[PDB]
Amino acid sequence: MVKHGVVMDVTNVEQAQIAEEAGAVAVMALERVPADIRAAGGVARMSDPALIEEIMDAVSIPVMAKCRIGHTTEALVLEAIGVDMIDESEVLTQADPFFHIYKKKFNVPFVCGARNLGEAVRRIWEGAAMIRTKGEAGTGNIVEAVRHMRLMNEAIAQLQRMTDEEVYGVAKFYANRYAELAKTVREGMGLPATVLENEPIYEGFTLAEIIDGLYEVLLEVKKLGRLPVVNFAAGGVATPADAALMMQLGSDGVFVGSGIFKSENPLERARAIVEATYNYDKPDIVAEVSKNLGEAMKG
Amino acid sequence: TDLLKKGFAKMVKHGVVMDVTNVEQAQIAEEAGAVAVMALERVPADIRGGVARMSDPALIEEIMDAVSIPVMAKCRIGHTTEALVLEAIGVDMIDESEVLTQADPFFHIYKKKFNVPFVCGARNLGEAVRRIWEGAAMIRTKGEAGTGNIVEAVRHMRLMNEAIAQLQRMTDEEVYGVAKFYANRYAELAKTVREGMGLPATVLENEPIYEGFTLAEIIDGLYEVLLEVKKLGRLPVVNFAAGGVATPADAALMMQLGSDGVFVGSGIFKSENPLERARAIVEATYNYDKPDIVAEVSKNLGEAMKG
Amino acid sequence: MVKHGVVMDVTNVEQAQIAEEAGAVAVMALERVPADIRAAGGVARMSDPALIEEIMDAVSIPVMAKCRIGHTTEALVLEAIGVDMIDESEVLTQADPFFHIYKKKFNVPFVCGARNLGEAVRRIWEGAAMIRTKGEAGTGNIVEAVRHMRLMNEAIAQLQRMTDEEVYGVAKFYANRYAELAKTVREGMGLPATVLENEPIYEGFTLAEIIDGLYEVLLEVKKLGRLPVVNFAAGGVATPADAALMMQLGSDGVFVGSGIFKSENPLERARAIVEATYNYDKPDIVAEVSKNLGEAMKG
Ligand SMILES: [Cl-]
Ligand SMILES: [Cl-]
Ligand SMILES: [Cl-]
Ligand SMILES: [Cl-]
Ligand SMILES: [Cl-]
Ligand SMILES: [Cl-]
Ligand SMILES: [Cl-]
Ligand SMILES: [Cl-]
Ligand SMILES: [Cl-]
């Protein structure tokens, strides 16, 4: 699993090689860049396995691929063809409106997006091995990534000031999202929209067991003062300064999709973002690589 | 028929039913491995600007003569006459579908008096139970035909499975309470009419409201179907997924969610390579628990549909 | 512990002996009959130990004594002088407005009043060895005893139709009464009137542990189809027919306070109620003993 660096979105062999040449730590194989996914519209699904394999053969760095949220068979396909990591992302069209994939039963690692601590804890409990503190992919606006990293940092800072009993109270609150389907159905059957805490609602787990599960993850967060899994910033990174900004905010690394290939000079731009990510604390370097970089993505 | 209706349905389970608009497609569907075809003038993706009605009987007969596998056809909801026409020309099964323009805003066809079996759509348990009590021999947990977005089909199967899981934890008295709630939909016309006559929008439970049945009798009917659902832990009839199946992985997903099979409309003929695509969906449906097979048939399929 | 029969309230040696002569299964020693306690007013407390001991020496049947609700030192005194059973009753002036005595740490058995299933379960969990389904002592009106026995029977009948998961939901609901003090105090400190389920609130037990505790008692009730401890009816029994009525409703026996000594012929009246309680299913006997019984308590 990647721990530092820049993960780049690529749509073909040429881009995958450009990414590696630039210094990417890994690539994200997909048929449509996020920026083009928001505009195009339609239903964005898992990419053709043949395209992903072609990319896997074209580079010597890890290859990631995304599947729709809740689409466990798309994920089983990506695992079967051997991708290094699956990204269950909101970038694509959600397949299951109630539940995310139960990632723990898979062998391949998953990276999941999260807008706040509650989402991160829930994704981690279901099996995520890496978290993507995302904002809004395809916009080229770093504010969304910043808003969420701020929300994440503040939530963790406040969690560290709580007693375990108060942390359990947070776990209990975060667990409610899992009972949404059960309550909706009960209402549809003419009964109150409530649930018993000892009835199965997700993968055989009862609300009570889910609470204990989120509680154990929150205790890890409290002890570490951060998420217990690698956490990269994503969505909106368009310039070397944006990348460096996310690192200063505590990100372990960054994901870049539209910012590179939707800009004027992809290779040069990519190298610059890679250098800024490794030297986020060196203004002179960030400044030099941003010099004469050319047009950046609109957004 | 009674036993013959469910007899036909059990032979289509585990397979893929494909929508076709002509002899060529029907034939492609057959060589692809479809268990049956759904004949119609325009696929759901195209259906969605005007009034979509039953297809010309001549077009359906041409399709029936072009293939050796069974053929189904659609009729508008509540359109008893269209259904009677389809039965007369000999289709193997009638699909009272919401993809077509609803003809009766108050009631669905009373399917029990027909000889030919019916397949009806359902968004949740309540709808499935009412369609089944009306006579449906098959249910398709519908979603959003024509969008190529599997989310709709998933939502409804999730709702169906969760409701059935909750039903099994109830006593018979509690199930009766659910049947009572489900039956209210049949009294809508009666209440609206009473209000129009200047009286409270209420109804007496012993007055006829549907096909001669009183609300009280309808509740007992729904109650009996619910008891069957409770005993079996699933619907008492074949249940297929329908909606946005556009890829082999989508079909495999529905099967893993418990579907007995899948209906594919726009996903095949609105794609780049119809025959190849159809073949891949058929194999993915038969081997939904085989990641390697699903992956294999997904490679180099070409562009799919969207919406 | 008594299992059948009539328990009578006595205020002196003469009454205690009358009670035994009549056939009482045990006596309840106190300085003021309930009917006179409601009228008199003032603060009703534990009786003088000397009076209780005099009664203990005057009879050959068990002697009970009451203490104020929550008054654990009054109870420790009754235990020290050797009473056979302590009755923590609402007949006397409540001493602790938040909690009842933690009866489990005592050696002597306790009998507690209950108006409904929730109260019975809570009293049983805190240690009660016997329950008194009471209505309104001192009134001579059997309706209060009947109302509560009806409420008790119906609640148990409905509990038997529930799954364990639903029973837990009832246990959770019944447990809330214990957090009243904690919520009041938090509000007094300027914070929301809420509590964390893992913080101590009663005898070191957290709300969560109390819930599991009430849940285990409810499972016993569900399995038995009745309370897991002896259950007598009390308050309002003034005639032989009243006693027989309570037995037909499912009572294991009856407590009689005002009905006997506040009537015209105590001894004769007491014997009649004893006979009616043992032959509650024999109208001819109930009728014969009610014949020429004389004036009954007003109320
Ligand atoms: Cl979430
Ligand atoms: Cl509960
Ligand atoms: Cl973190
Ligand atoms: Cl309906
Ligand atoms: Cl009526
Ligand atoms: Cl089913
Ligand atoms: Cl209480
Ligand atoms: Cl809590
Ligand atoms: Cl009882």
Image (cartoon, coloured by chain):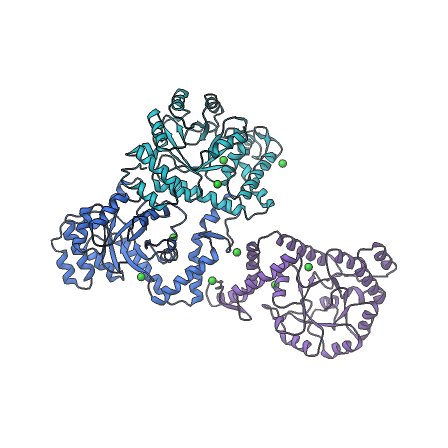
Chain colours: A blue, B cyan, C purple
Q: Residue furthest top?
A: B58
- For residue C63, above or below residue A212: below
Question: Where ligand 7 lies, by quadrant?
Answer: bottom right
What quarter of the picture does the N terminus of chain B occupy? top right
Q: Quadrant of residue B272?
A: top left
Side (left or right) of A255 relative to C20: left
Quarter of the image with the C terminus of chain B is: top left
Q: What is the x, y in percent for residue A77?
A: 33, 46
- Name the residue furthest right: C292
Is C217 or C138 nearer to us in this picture? C217
Which corner quadrant of the image does residue A159 belong to? bottom left
Vertical comparison of C88 with A55: above or below: below
Residue A68 in sight here: no
Is C281 left or right of C149, judged from the image as shown?
Answer: right
Q: Is residue C137 above or below residue A298?
A: below
Residue B190 visible in rendering? yes
Along the horizontal axis of the image, is C166 left or right of A6? right
**Number of disc labels:** 0
Please state which of residues A45 and B212 is positioned toward the viewer in this rendering: A45
Viewed as shown, does residue B90 lie left or right of C214? left
Rendering coords of residue B249 (x, y %): 35, 42
Which residue is situated farthest in the left direction here? A292
Residue closest to the eye, B271 or B48: B271
Image coords of residue C217 (percent x, y) = 61, 62
**Image x and y of residue B105, in percent:** 48, 30
The residue closer to the viewer here, A244 or A182, is A182
